[PDB]
Image (cartoon, coloured by chain):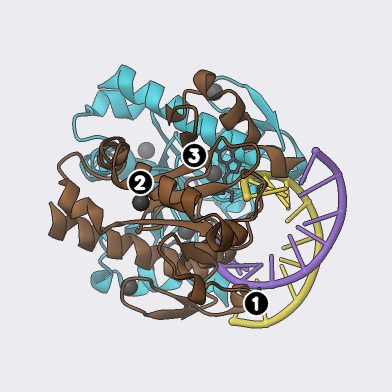
Chain colours: A cyan, B brown, C yellow, D purple
Amino acid sequence: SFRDNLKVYIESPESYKNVIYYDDDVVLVRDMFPKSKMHLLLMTRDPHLTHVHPLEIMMKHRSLVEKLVSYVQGDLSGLIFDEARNCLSQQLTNEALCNYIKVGFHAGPSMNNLHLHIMTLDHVSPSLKNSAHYISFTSPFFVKIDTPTSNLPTRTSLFQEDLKCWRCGETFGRHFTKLKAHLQEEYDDWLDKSV
Amino acid sequence: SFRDNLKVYIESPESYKNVIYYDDDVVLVRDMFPKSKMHLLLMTRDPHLTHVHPLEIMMKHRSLVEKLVSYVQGDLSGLIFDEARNCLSQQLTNEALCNYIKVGFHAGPSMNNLHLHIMTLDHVSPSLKNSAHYISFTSPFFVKIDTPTSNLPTRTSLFQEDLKCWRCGETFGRHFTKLKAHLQEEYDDWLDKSV
DNA sequence: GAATCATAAC
DNA sequence: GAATCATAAC
Ligand SMILES: Nc1nc2c(ncn2[C@@H]2O[C@H](CO)[C@@H](O)[C@H]2O)c(=O)[nH]1
Ligand SMILES: Nc1nc2c(ncn2[C@@H]2O[C@H](CO)[C@@H](O)[C@H]2O)c(=O)[nH]1
Ligand SMILES: [Cl-]
Ligand SMILES: [Cl-]
Ligand SMILES: [Cl-]
Ligand SMILES: [Cl-]
Ligand SMILES: [Zn+2]
Ligand SMILES: [Zn+2]
C-alpha cells in the first residue's frame, strides 16, 4: 500500500537520483513532498528496525538513534549543509545553517519504514498544503531526536488546535493561508539577517 | 458582498499601493490573486458601464472595448512590459513579451465591476489552486478582447472537461497537480529560450 | 471570488 | 502519505 512507498529507497538506493547518500546501514534521500525549503529523510536499511515504531526506537534502540545522530552531525553534515545551501541560498555558512535545521521522527508516521526528518525550520514550500502538515512538524507530534525518554509523547488531537508561528508565536487560529503568508515573511526576514 | 470587492479601485485608486495607473477613465491594478506570474486588471471608472456584463460590452459598447485596447497597446504598454519584467525576468525585451501576454474578459465574471485581464500566458502561480481557475483563462470562458462578435460564446460546462496544456496540447485528464508540474516545465523552457 | 473542512479511492 | 471533489459561510 501507500504506507510502503519508502521501501524502494532502502532496497535499491543506487538507482534513485533523489538519493544523496547510501551505504550498508543508511540512506539519505530528498523527500518527494518537502515541507520546508530543505527536507531530507535518513532511513535505516536494517530489516529488523525499519518496521519498528519510532517511539519504540527512542525507548528501546538507543544505539540506532545514536548512529543516526552520528551520521547527521558527522559524515553527512557536509552533504546536508551543501543541500541546504542549494535549497535556500548559496552564501549561507554552516554556522548560519546549524541552528536553522531540525531533526526528528513523526510520533505517528504514515509510512511504515523508519525515517528520520532533516529539514530547515522555515516551512516555506508549495508541498505544505494544510494545517495538519504544519502541526505535524511544529508540535510534540514532531519528536525531536534529542528528546529525553522521560519526555516522549503518547495519547492525537493537536491537529484540531490553533496555528502558531514557530518563530515568534503569533496565532492564526485555523487560518492556514494567513499562516503561509507569515511563514514567507519570517523566512525573508531570517534570510536577510543571515546573509 | 464579495462580488463588489473591486469597487474600491475605481472609487479610490489614489490610495491603493497595488494600483499601477489611474486617470479619469480607467484603473490598472495588480490582481490580488494572480493566476499567472503577471496578472493585471484594467477597470473602467465609468459608472454606467462598470456594471454592464462583458458580453454586452463586446456586443454593444465597441467604443469602450477600443478605448481599453488603446490603453493596453499604447499609453500603458510601458508600464505593462516593465511589470512583466518585474514578475518574470528582468532581461526580457518587449518583443519577447508581446506574444506572451493575453488580454480578455471572463464570460461569467464573479465580480460585478467590469475588469479586463492582462496577464502572462504561463499560469505559473501559487494562487492558481484548482482546475476551474485554469479552465477559466484557457478555454472559451476567456473571451479574448479581439474576439469577433460573431464568435462570442454563450450557454457553462467547460469546467468538467479535461485539462490541456495551453502551449503544447498535452492532456492531463482531471489531474491538476500533474498539470501544475507541466506548466512550470513549459515556463522554464520558454524562459530559457527567451533570455 | 477565497478558504476551511470532510470525504472517497489509491 | 497525495489529490480530486463537494460543501458552508463570507
Ligand atoms: N522521497 C519520498 N518521500 C515521500 C514519498 N511519499 C511520501 N513521502 C514523504 O515521506 C513523509 C512520510 O511521513 C512525508 O513527508 C511525505 O511527504 C515518496 O514516495 N518519496
Ligand atoms: N486586485 C484584486 N483582485 C481581486 C480581488 N478579489 C478578487 N480578485 C480577482 O479578480 C478576479 C475576478 O474575476 C479574479 O482573478 C480574482 O482573483 C481583490 O480584492 N483585489
Ligand atoms: Cl551520536
Ligand atoms: Cl496561498
Ligand atoms: Cl484600439
Ligand atoms: Cl503542487
Ligand atoms: Zn512569526
Ligand atoms: Zn505543454
Q: Quadrant of residue B20?
A: top left
Q: In the figure, is residue A9 to the left or right of B135?
A: left
Left or right of B137 in this view: A59? right
- Distance from Cα at disc 3 to Cα at disc 1: 52 Å
- Circle 3 crowding by C-alpha within 10 Å: few under 14, some 14–19, many from 20: some
- D3, A25: nearer the viewer: D3
Q: Residue A160 falls in which quadrant of the image?
A: top right
Respond whether the residues carrying marks 2 and 1 are from the same subunit. Answer: yes
Image: A121 above or below C6: above
The amino acid marked with disc number 1 is Ser
Q: Which residue is mark 2?
A: B70
**Relative image position of residue A147 (x, y in whole percent):** 55, 34
Q: Is residue A175 left or right of residue A109?
A: right
| Mark 3 → mark 2, Cα distance in angstroms | 63 Å
Q: Chain of mark 1?
A: B
Residue B3 at x, y = what percent? 71, 44
At which x and y percent is residue B31? Answer: 50, 41
Chain letter for mark 2, please: B
As shown in the figure, which amino acid type bears the numbered disc 2? Ser
Q: Judging from the image, what secondary structure is the residue with disc 3 in?
A: loop
Q: Nearer the viewer, mark 2 or mark 1?
A: 2
Secondary element at tag 2: helix
Residue at point 46% right, 57% down?
B104
The reply to whether the residue tagged 2 has its Cβ within 8 angstroms of ligand 5 is: yes
* Chain for disc number 3: A
Q: Secondary structure at mark 1?
A: loop
Q: Dot 3 corresponds to which residue?
A: A145
Percent across and percent down for residue B54 are 59, 56
State the CA–CA distance, disc 2 to disc 1. Answer: 33 Å
Crowd class of label 1 (few under 14; some 14 to 19; many from 20; radius 10 Å):
few
Residue named by callout 1? B157
Q: State whether residue B173 appears in this view.
A: yes
